[PDB]
View 1 (cartoon, rainbow over the protein chains, first blue to last red):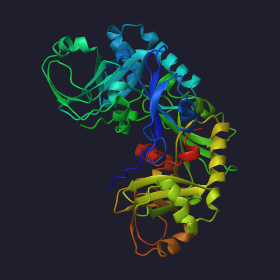
View 2 (tube, rainbow over the protein chains, first blue to last red; view 1 turned 45 degrees about the vertical axis):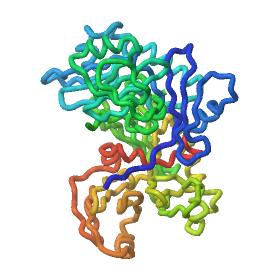
View 3 (cartoon, each protein chain N blue to C red; view 1 turned 135 degrees about the vertical axis):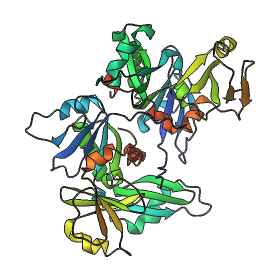
View 4 (cartoon, rainbow over the protein chains, first blue to last red; view 1 turned 90 degrees about the vertical axis):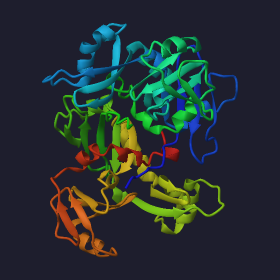
Length: 236
Length: 236
């Protein structure tokens, strides 16, 4: 009965610091530049500016700039999750509540999973998109584009930094040297499917045939549903 | 293991003739105007123009303006489905191939399901969206927003016209008087789940608790994946 609609062609882009060139890759099965990839800016005569005018963009941002939280909606309280979040999560925010953007990832009755990020970061990422003529269809924490095949976790490297997907609605970002501390600051050891060569770290690392983050994202379009484009950032 | 991401808030709009006011409804669970609806233009002091600036839009267009076709990609031919479509389907088009827009809905190896529509209609619908500040996230034939719960078909009325979803990748649009002919121009009789009061027509019509088209669409966000925003219409 599944419709199994044919996947949407798109330009997948990962943004991080404004100072660094972004990563991009085209997902357009059957089309001439399918799987083309690159960086921007660059001195190469890149097709990126043309692709930005021809395809919608799925934008990934760094999980290191996000915070993932669970919360319980108080019994009898009829306020929506994103109004409850700033009040309940205030003690877990580095920034003032007014300086923080919240997005809802999942809800099961009273239990909500959210992502918090600085409003200024949202503004700067979206300004960069506009300056590049990128039309974002979703804005997703990068770690949430990784496969979720529990009970194993997933991992990949992007610019030496490890992205580790350890739960359905969150993940971690770590420098190679933190893994021992992070993976053993955690309660127990785990099994990790690694899409980059495994590091010497705690846990059972299973080396998968290597794939880049943007390739993993292209194979996981459902992850587009996990998006920070909510509330004041719902639409340009 | 399912992520079951929380559904995206959006403005659902159905466009038809430029001369007719569109239908709109807000899908924004927990927010103040959730399920608000109306027409545009109107002399009511409608929230529509503000909603268009605050939420992305899912735009539905009439199935009566679309044609749904199956095709088989020739063996050994490496051309993409949307390049093969105009050549194979030429004899089934009312308009010249050059005047026709094609979109891919589904592919299973050599078998493809497409939708064909006049390029001018696409231009006019998208121009109307731009004039109204609607930012379309998808553009879907209305009949494809109906439930697909086989082996039964689905049906609902919109402005007296019946929309009947009879296959996973297509549907029909009919005036009340054509149903006898259409439902008995068909091979056999069928079971039809009707979200409007059933008409006196062939088949077994099962009256469901009544729902409007836009309400049915709001409950079926997966249908956003069935979209005419491909090729030259992939992005504004």
